[PDB]
Image 1 (cartoon, rainbow over the protein chains, first blue to last red):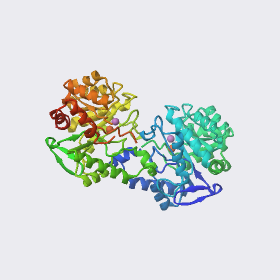
Image 2: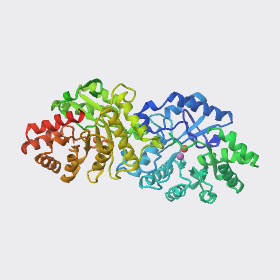
Image 3: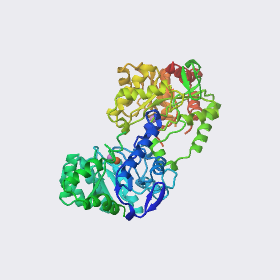
Image 4: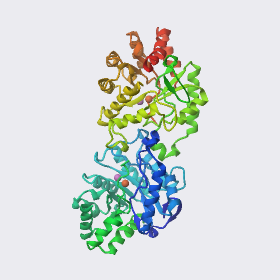
Length: 292
Length: 292
Ligand SMILES: [Co+2]
Ligand SMILES: [Co+2]
Ligand SMILES: [Fe+3]
Ligand SMILES: [Fe+3]
């Protein structure tokens, strides 16, 4: 019941070891359209294929790629990467903005925004039959602006209609993650269908625990570390493994490796007493629940 | 010495009757990339061809199209319109933003922004040999923000290196047009190489005259009218014809006709005592000077 790029859909129970937040490529759509001389698609493709192959060599079965509007989602690029690797790849829909929406959205309703996400979930992405399996939204240093709130409310409509989960970008040093969770739950989204991202950027463990205690997954998803690993280990030590999702990604708005989790983070956890049942919770059971 | 889409360049003295600010098409790059189902390129092409043909039937020889980053500039679409009509079309470079730049520009210098404009002027647009003949920039209700100022300063660098003129979008109800003119002239741009646009939206004639008196062209370029025609006529009556540029465009950020000037504005002017020497000043001599 999870759509996959270039493949038939799969049951959530079969997702296996999952990297929940990794971008194959990211760019600003208007800059790439206007100044293509700044970009090399062939290098981007080779890098993405190599990274996915490296992840598969460490046992990754599924990658969730939350590149959406604002970060250059390209479903045809994603399909080429799948053809070259055989990875299960989950694409999403959504909008990443920090202040205002593009000019297109002037005088358009929240429902019209939600209809875009629902189109991608139910019909397909960018004129293909590859469907979106989650909604991605953001807020950062400017906080919850008028347009940021519109996108959050549209994500809630899409989740209520289609049941796909919601992944967020937040700024770990303000309350944007807590606000995203509150607005979405007030609109009727199940808290366990939300992943509040980019929380590994803060050592304020009480803030992180507050979000998890309210029922949502917490994205310790900036790996690339000790303070992050310390915070991660402390959160694990304190019993929060069933809310933790771990990734590297580095933010797609930035126009390190996808296996640094295997070379740095997981070893560090293991040598500090984290057993293999916790690793399986974080990388298999938590994504299965999120997508269930 | 003016580059033309799909043609050899022309001397500025041969530009003839010119429409200084008309968009063949406009859209938000990220929305079109992400949701192509919202758009019909074949309808857009038919509309653009018909509009250009209608303009040519009224004697227009050259159209300046200030669609740039933020409004969906597409040099290959423009070339198809030229092939279908034979119009002289001047394309530009630049960036239209009201608050912040796309994520690409985080931690990038003004010089790097200017290098993009200079690339389009000296090398070509979007991988073609069609070159940009002017720079287009904007500011609106948020005023001169940090990123808006960066783009203005980059435009000044591009003009100083290449001598192409600068067209602006401004908000007629604040001082953004006056501020654009001041910042550009402080950076060494000749005032007569600047067109401050969207001033037809205000009846504050003293503000408009202040900009013209400082040496820049004033864009009475929102046609589509009486109050605009009244303001235009009053400005003509007061001796400002040699600073007036007239167009319709309607702003490209809006994702009426290009001949409404011939069906409404020019007739109205003529029947109110405006002779044919003024019409020639506004539509032939002023563009020739601007591009000289
Ligand atoms: Co992010
Ligand atoms: Co405008
Ligand atoms: Fe990300
Ligand atoms: Fe315009």
